[PDB]
Length: 171
Image (cartoon, helix red, strand yellow):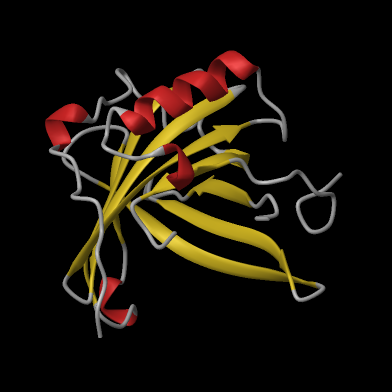
């Protein structure tokens, strides 16, 4: 019925990891950081990336909800340039007309920063996630995650750091 979101930033303000290596990005990643213009404590979730033969990703989200492990699998389709992706079978997602994925930065074996933008029910949402190969990351990376977010118009109260857990995501 109604909603008010912080304008999505122009893509030019969103870097792209150069010479992106899709194979090395495969595997599990913990969501240590999450920022978004989305609606206003969160337990940590994980995202497993698997490179299919056709080089598109099978991404599985895993979270601990209501005492159970809830799984969700999406399909990331290589976009206009390496490190960028689009959502597969988008028509199976009610009211979703656009979905963009752009790997901002990553050393592949420790951390990554991913930028997400989508159009759902005509409302434009965007978000940045700080992923770590481990549930914990150096403060310096978190600080850089925080600065990046803010540089995109997002206030601190829109930047949360999920609390690490053991259930479902392995501990």
